[PDB]
Image 1 (cartoon, rainbow, N blue to C red):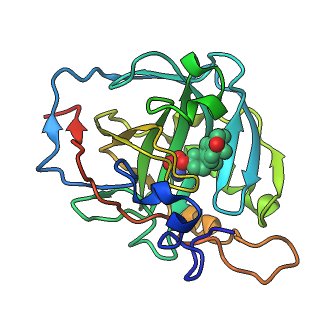
Image 2: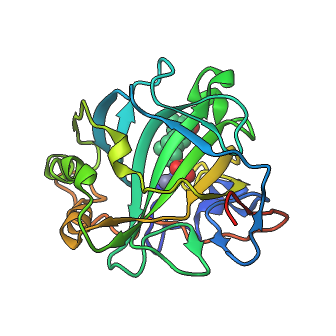
Length: 257
Ligand SMILES: C[C@@H]1CC(=O)[C@@]2(C)CC[C@H]3[C@@H](CC[C@@H]4C[C@H](OS(N)(=O)=O)CC[C@@]43C)[C@H]12
Ligand SMILES: [Zn+2]
């Protein structure tokens, strides 16, 4: 029922998901001058060498690459985190044009897209239990700007024609998510939420300062996806981003000076 349109988009979500007006909603604007450098923050540990990708799926609100999270193979540790977080999936949010698409903003700047690598805390045993906990999930957010191609994204772009409509999936084995990371792991962190329904307040956000560059041809392929199922009136999957929500009583911390 929910979506990104005039009649079912972000301003409607609170009716089915009243936590939409809660105290730790995401995304937020990152005011770079107000974010406090925290020398106590650890470097982020991204251990993706044994990652096992399984499938690529159009879920009607994004496309996602799902991983085997039945063991500690692709894990996030350190940074602001206590314990070990398993990679479940990554997905993107993007715009109809390059001047919008990101969920987080930086001094009100919107990027063309935002990559979310979703991880869950192994102390809760499964992701369904983890989404009920304030420290259940860690989402690594990476901004995309348009310029030079990202070679590590091309394997993803080239299969999107096979998952055009809601509910379509394909084999997507042997994909290495290290190819989607920028040079620097400098980050901002704050306590927040899932950015789609059910908007659960279960996420430690880790947003990288350094964007990755993708080509116009790569983001054009995102924009050919469809929100609709096959047969249904064609509605391009564009502008699948929630705007910035009130920061309320929260501090954004920077890992860097
Ligand atoms: C599988 C877990 C358990 C659960 O209840 C689910 C299904 C809610 C929806 C979640 C999913 C985890 C992966 C995604 C995270 C995304 O949030 S974001 N955009 O902040 O990264 C919201 C959409 C998403 C599919 C959750
Ligand atoms: Zn997301």
